[PDB]
Length: 201
Length: 211
Image (tube, rainbow over all chains, first blue to last red):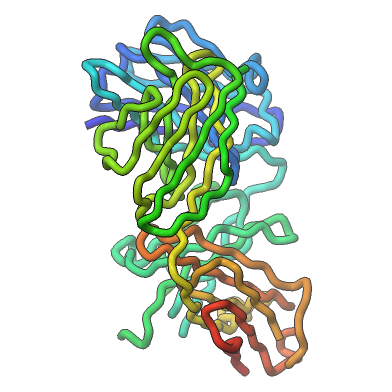
């Protein structure tokens, strides 16, 4: 079973550096070219770079050339993307992907889950969690940067759950709510950028 | 760089009706006996998924309702009968020349029947009251279409102190949900707090309030 697992994203100041990693398991890594593709929040897909099985590579020049460097370690089945001289417009979710693999007359294509890179001068801040009691939910207020993840009963309850897109308040901090409807029938917040976890009944 | 132009950018389609998305390039995508254009579908919160490779070949696992055609600089993705699970953004991409370039993406919206929202009001929590700010939230659950008016009212209509957030179309019932948050410091000085919802599915606006 093929899996592309990304890591190394997070918050960094403009002009700083980050190093993304994509560990490939269950797949003959050394025999294929790999790509990085990014997506700014609310925008489309943009191809970033490719590295062939030889080790030769190319970059989207008009946006990242001279600042990003793609590499591979075949002994560790891992793809890398070194991001230097970061700019605000580099904020995006970054995917490692094979793109189209066409061989033996079948077409396959594998993608990682993506890792979010945020380029900003603002400081990290953990969220406050306030209960929304009667439908019911949790209010996740005043955090930066994106993202937060919200589960219900440690991820057991998933039916009827609506977690809303975060909204940037005028203070520069994000805020969202995650609700679940119970019409008189009868939350686990994780903010990795601040290393904060809160459980609110 | 090859420019990929997708049309249309937004495509509202009722379930059971066909859909057609076109993709134009500024350079021929032919090499040998293949056109190097692929179609992807990206659902909310997920990675892109290959649908059609090399212009007209259905990827493994893709249902037969999806098909691709075209050659040279003109390509078309078709869904014979769209279903609720087809909601998402569709992209074409050329791979005949590096740098690989994507189309702008086509947001396919599912046109279901009108559905009225369920309105809920939540007062600020005691934990939050121990801080300096009060947040009142108004919930509009499972409605369609997205167009909806939320207004906050001691019977005084508010303006400038609210923010809205709307979920993506649900993959099952194709409905939206919306939340509106009223932020005040001033809160303890008033008694009546109400949010009034206006939507096509409601014969008359619905108001949910607390004291």
